[PDB]
Image (cartoon, rainbow over all chains, first blue to last red; front, side, top):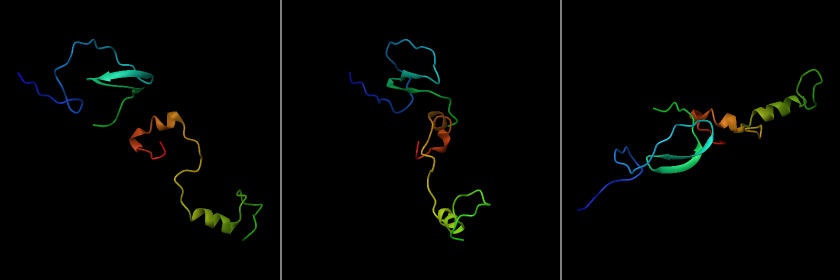
Length: 48
Length: 48
């Protein structure tokens, strides 16, 4: 069996077992979005 | 024209005012606040 996929560049609907939390804004936090991890401040955006 | 005029608010002379008007600078304050940069993101400021 050969599994093929792509990572951290487009929408995804298959994920590992993890618990999601609530969204914190205007505060420096560690974040993990669909596997992309980092640190920063999250604000609402006007981009479409 | 080459000496400052007490009447005008400016402390420079007329020709000095012309000279300062002829050169354009990206910014002059040397002060850019975190709130200013975070809140004008849509502008994509080079200084930010």
